[PDB]
Length: 269
Ligand SMILES: Nc1ccn([C@@H]2O[C@H](COP(=O)(O)OP(=O)(O)O)[C@@H](O)[C@H]2O)c(=O)n1
Ligand SMILES: [Mn+2]
Ligand SMILES: [Mn+2]
Image 1 (tube, rainbow, N blue to C red):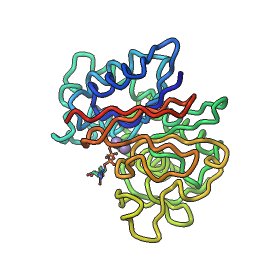
Image 2: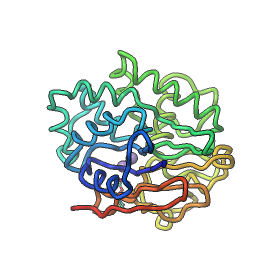
Image 3: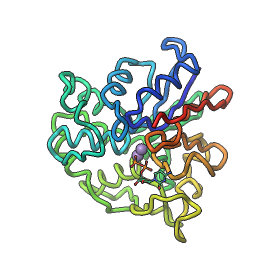
């Protein structure tokens, strides 16, 4: 079976309980994870250890908090106490875990299921070939020996409009924001980097990225996490918002792809 779970945010106990609920069995089943494995919840260390151990039985995409952890580890960014990353950063296997983490994709595609996953979704300004090329470029920088230079370069809110003519720092910044921070779009598809509330309580003319017709969403189902204030609600057919805010006292959601059956684990907090 194929299971897809939204942002775990260090909620190891809930993750394992949800996987036991569905009798998740590596070798017979595959797990897709929307990223943001770490931060806020208490068990980022255990989460990364487990997910790395799954190997080919897990398909991960990196989220914005995974990238932030990598930046903290590399000495690029400051550790925020509320993220609760210190046990992971101080672990004897921190190098192994984080060097594995930075090698993981930004984008997962399964052609037989016509299914795409990224942390925040797929901007309507991208077709599939462009999304793939952009994921490859940023994955290449993250898996290289020079990844701390990219992590430093990644921070920024501009440019927020895609063009194939974008080059250099702006190109990588837009790519990173589209895959890991996107929520609202302007009517022309341009990213808004500030509003993080639910679609109903957002100011006009902002609309969810998935409310703007785009070439990937026309052909593929898209699963994503990231947007906790969405509460997994209000998406169009073929769009699966899996982040139901476990670390926030919400729930951890798992979708089984074959029958579109949902399973939910209450937050322990
Ligand atoms: N149900 C919720 C959950 C979070 N939030 C807020 O949304 C902001 C972004 O958090 P998020 O969980 O959606 O995304 P990430 O920061 O994990 O990437 C936080 O500052 C939360 O306070 C909200 O307004 N409503
Ligand atoms: Mn998140
Ligand atoms: Mn996120």
